[PDB]
Image 1 (cartoon, rainbow, N blue to C red):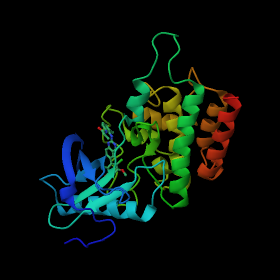
Image 2 (image 1 turned 90 degrees about the horizontal axis):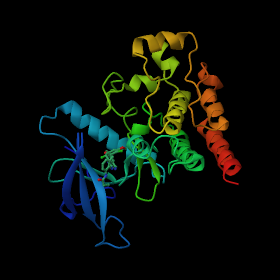
Image 3 (image 1 turned 135 degrees about the horizontal axis):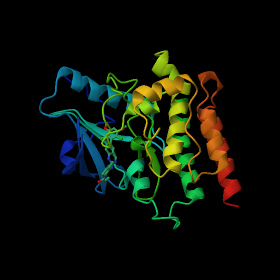
Image 4 (image 1 turned 180 degrees about the vertical axis):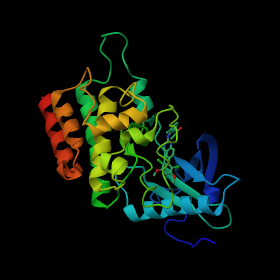
Length: 288
Ligand SMILES: *CCC(=O)Nc1cccc(C)c1Nc1ncc2cc(-c3c(Cl)c(OC)cc(OC)c3Cl)ccc2n1
């Protein structure tokens, strides 16, 4: 069973399914008449569906993610829900499709060779960071705690709009496995805050810690956090107050905000609202 939510319901026959994107499995599609102002117009979207092997639990995960997306609402800096297909077939959840892929691969693809300068100068990297903070400010105001904020979960559109992905999984029924390898072989637990790692508690300020790590990923052009360090010793270092060094090409304002994001005590970290305003002021400092 699945109830008709008429206003989110999109007829599945107006989708032309295309290339698999990844893995719950995801396909690119063309959708006709997403915006009812031009009802025959094609747009490109991403469609999520269950795999053949799926259990009750997998269905509940996809459904719960869809329902949290409905509740959270739309914002320019997040992957927005566009539609769902729940009648007369398998469940499809339809979302915005970001043509340049994830921010980690985007950054890594644009690292310059040797000392030669690259396209992604300080103001560009700061603007990126600002966009991510605006998305997170939005999520924060909607009482959403991400639990896996990282460059791999930020997608880049054709117009270089940064969009937060996978923000429905925590309030959803899905259990995040922080020891499940990224496509890169890295471990998500390297973005988790010490209160979650040691005290087993998550707060709104836990995502701020993760944002600090994401800042570091940005200014290293898609580098691996705590490079060289196996998680076991990483965790003992984090006991003694170890923090990542300022990366080689980074404005001091941004390292300053990283250090603030990485206060041991969650209650001492800034909010995304404060972070948005701070990055707005850095951009102006730097670009004028
Ligand atoms: C848009 C055309 C394209 O080829 N895009 C593409 C190629 C290679 C890698 C990536 C990451 C993409 N873009 C892309 N854009 C948006 C995506 C959105 C999701 C997604 C889904 Cl399907 C759901 O389903 C409920 C929920 C999400 O988070 C709230 C997200 Cl982020 C998956 C993959 C996407 N890929």
